[PDB]
Image (cartoon, rainbow over all chains, first blue to last red; front, side, top):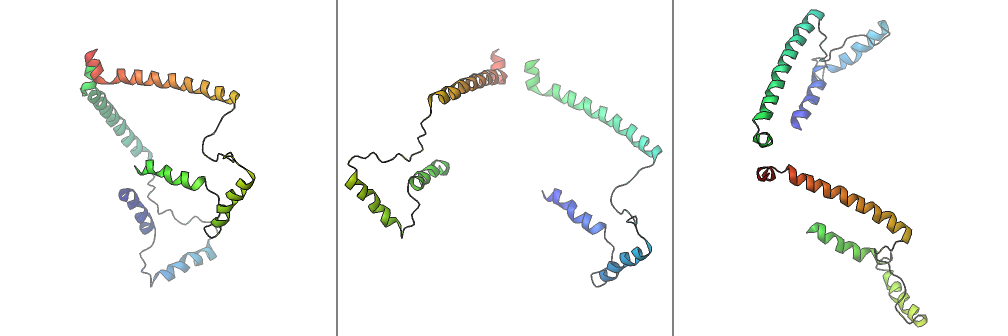
Length: 89
Length: 89
């Protein structure tokens, strides 16, 4: 639960500028003077959310399918090593 | 034990009128003036004790036998799935 709760602190504290709370009041206005120039919420997406290039995605997804079939042969072998399967055998 | 003890509080507190203990003294006499008119203890049975109509009882007991044979085939199957039966097999 604390492992699950641990992410909720970091999403608050990452996507937030490094100003101290005496200096966080300036950044409260920094996004308002921006909307005297801007008009649409299209500033930035400082989320985790890592988009990938096309030639790297197939450079990862080919690697992961190869690791899936390596895993699936283990559970298929670990099922055969369970002795209650062998009595059924 | 507390699950078993839990019913003994409710049988006391259900079959008893809703008068507060300043007003429970009136209901102490309400059943006595009744026996200046009545003579036999045949007032009411405010117990759990739900009697059923005849066409609803067969509307329940046909449903329960069907659920019994559904249960009995499970334990007969769960006995066969126990591995110590399979070594006897």
